[PDB]
Structure formats: structure tokens, C-alpha cells
Amino acid sequence: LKRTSFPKKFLFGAGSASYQYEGAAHIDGRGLSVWDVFTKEHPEKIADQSNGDVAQDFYHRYKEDIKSMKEMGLESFRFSISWSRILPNGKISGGINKLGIKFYNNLIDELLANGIKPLVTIYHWDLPQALQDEYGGFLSPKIVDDFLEYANLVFKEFGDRVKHWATLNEPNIMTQQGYVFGAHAPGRCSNCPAGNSGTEPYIVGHHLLLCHAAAFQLYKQKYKDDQKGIIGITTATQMAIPLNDNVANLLAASRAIDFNIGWFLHPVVYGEYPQTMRERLGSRLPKFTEKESEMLKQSFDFIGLNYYSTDYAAASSNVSYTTDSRATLSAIKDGVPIGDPTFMSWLHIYPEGILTLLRYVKERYNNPFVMITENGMADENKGSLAEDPMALKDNVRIRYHREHLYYVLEAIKEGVNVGGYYAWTWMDDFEWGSGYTPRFGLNFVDFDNDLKRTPKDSYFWFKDFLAN
Image (cartoon, rainbow, N blue to C red; front, side, top):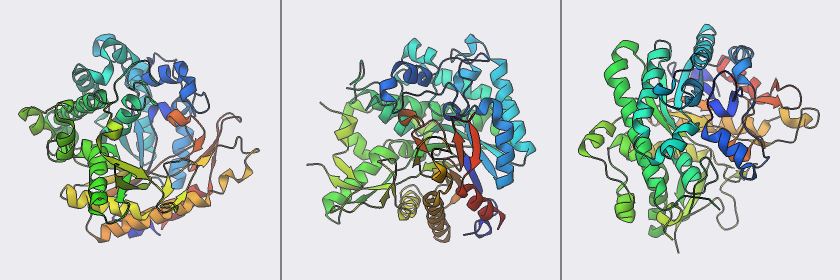
């Protein structure tokens, strides 16, 4: 495969998120996020009882990393802004942390100095704890005005240089894990000290979409004419295919797609929830005003798709999101995995499924401009480079990226409007509930050797790929 086989305007990048990368969590005026609290106060929910206090210390070492990015030939770099680093209490009334602004200014100036276009995710799950304490964060409509003022500050201070934005990253996972399974911050579920897995997800999702629409409309009306950038939304797009060709399994696949992918994509393309969510949930699903519906319809310049794997969907043989779809997912059919299993239980290697996703999005949503904002896989963390000499020989990762890009190039030949691909992830990082147990990086991070970065074989494959 060769980069010259892709459109010249197509963006090739690698991605990062604030809490997963930065460290310096309690220095330089940064306020607590719900993830500081979640990792510190629920270590039993983190596979290795770890946190993001230090991560890979990107906050201090970004200059060295960006040099390694330029050497690989990276076109774009995706990174997220820590709300609580710039606004310690989440509110403009709480004061703007100048050292936080300084850090993002330095990061951005460093990327552009090295010829790398920033793609900035405004919100990648690190909500200020002060907002969760004040009104339960995304459980309240008050989040929208606090999100608006945050988005406004971000556009005003960085938008002169930043020309590519995502409002949100994977609000579906953020809502599912945060408020259905309580496996992610803020750890609410219907075992959880508080929550309702049947009601709270649909409220949280509602307020996320209202935040998205308010940030989009603000960018359109106040900043787009001057700054000439673009703004979209990234969602998690695990694909579903029917277990078989039984009409019930065809509809189960449709219902799992509507409940996971369509949940946020339907409002942003058409201005309404998927009708199968309205049919199932009645009053548990909040209703958009005519105004809101107008603000949401085509509230994007692009849609970010985060594609890792596909499952089989079958029709389903104390209300919760989990059972609301009337569908069962599995990666196995007649005791045969959909693709090679990897360290992550939910990640089978099924590169065909990314074309299936891109075809579905094309046909369902009238071929909107999309980017793959995440795609990659993880090897198990087996310790230091000395403990794991084979960590660098990531032939499986190399195969994963190669076959997925083959199918993205197929997508382009079929007139799908895909214009970006961002690897997950630049360097081994903090992976939420999994802690540092999964290594997703093109770069190895030796957490026992002063966070030394060693390029994996995948780095050199991407170097060759981008050069030709």
C-alpha cells in the first residue's frame, strides 16, 4: 500500500487524548477530572489499579515526541483539551488557568512548526469533577452553558491556528461505560453506589447532543467565517452484521446499529433519534424541541468514525440500555471467531467490517464527509523492553493497519466520502478501565525506564507507507 494511492487532501494521522497521555495531573493549576477521581477512588475498576497522574508525561515531553512524528512523516495529529486544565472548576467564573492555555498554545505551535496539522477534540471524557459535584455533570441541562463557554474559550484562543475540531469523542462509550455499566467515570449503574442503567444513559446522551449542537452552532455563527476551519463529532462505530439471513437477525443488526451508532449519528444528520429508539423507550427517551432539532440537523463538517471490530447480531430471546435493543452481540458464529481475537476481548481482526461500516454510513446518512478518527489494536503489556524484547515486532499491528487501509481505499473507489484515517495510538498509553495493560502504540513506552519511547516496527511501516 502507498500514501500516493490516497487523495492528496486525505489526512493521515495518529491520535491521543488528554487524560491518556499528558500526566502533570495535579500541577500547574489543573483541576480534578472525573477520571482522576474514578482511578484514585475506584482502583478495583482499573485492571492494574493505575491512574493518569503521570501517564507518558506528554505535558513535558511533547517536543521530543513531535520530532519523532515529523521523522515518521505524520500529516495530522489528533489530541484533546483537558477542560479542567484550562478551567479548574469547569466554569469561566472559576478563572482561566493561564498555564493550561500556555501548554495547548505550545503544543499547537510545535505541531505547526513541524508541518503537522492539529485535529482537536474539545471533550474526550475528562469532565471537571467540580461539574459532576455541582449538578451531576451530563445528568443536568446546566452542562450545555458550561460546555458552550468552554467551546467558546477554546475557539477564541486556539482557532487562529487550529482548523480541524471534534466537539465530542465517543459519547456512546462515555454514556454506556459511565452510566450503564459504571465501568468508566463517573461509575453510575442500576455494582454501583448510584445510577439507573434504564433512564440516565438517555438523559446523558441528550445533554451530550445539546452540547455538540451548541458548540457547532457557535463555531458556524461566530468563528467559521474568520478562522476558516471545520468541526465535526467522533463516535464509536463497532459494526454489527446479522448472525445469519433470518429476517429477525437482519432487524436485530439494524436495531444494534441504531442503538449504538445511530443514537448520536441520527440527531446530527437528520435532527431526530433513530425511530427504533423512539418505538422502544417512549418517555425514557427525551424529545428535541423544534429549535434543537433545527440546530442538530447537519451539525457537522465531518463525522469521525472509531472502528476497531465487528460483531454478529441476533434477535433477543429491570429496564436497561443493555436489553433495550432487543439484540444479542457475539464475535463467534458456530464456534468460529468473526476474526482473529487480540488482547482486547471486543477486538477481533475483521478489516472487511470497516468497508461494511463505510457502506452503511454512506447509504443510511446520504454519504456524509467521514474520517476514521481511530483504528488500531493492542498487544498485552508484558513489562519493560528488557522483560518483553518482542514488543517491537508488532507484525500483527502492521497487518491490522495494512488490511484496514486496503478496505478504506476500497471505500474511496466506491465513492464513499472518507477523507481521513487516524491510528490509535501514537504511543502506549492509559486505556481507562484497562489501565496500562493494553499497548496500542506505534511507539513502545517503557514505564520502568523513565517512559522511554522506542519506535515499534509499525512506526517504520507507516514511515515507508507515508513516503511512497
